[PDB]
Image (cartoon, rainbow, N blue to C red; front, top):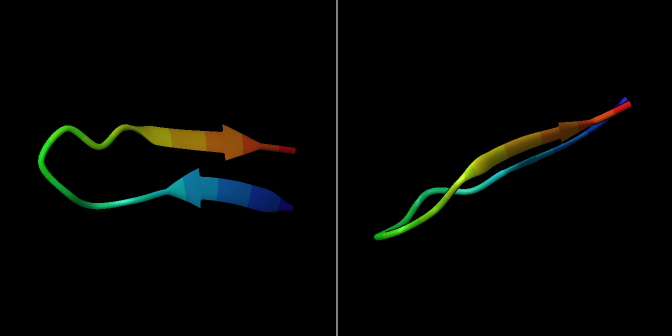
Length: 17
């Protein structure tokens, strides 16, 4: 389980697993 979610002007939400 390893997600890649970030917040900010122009940030995308990704998920890996």
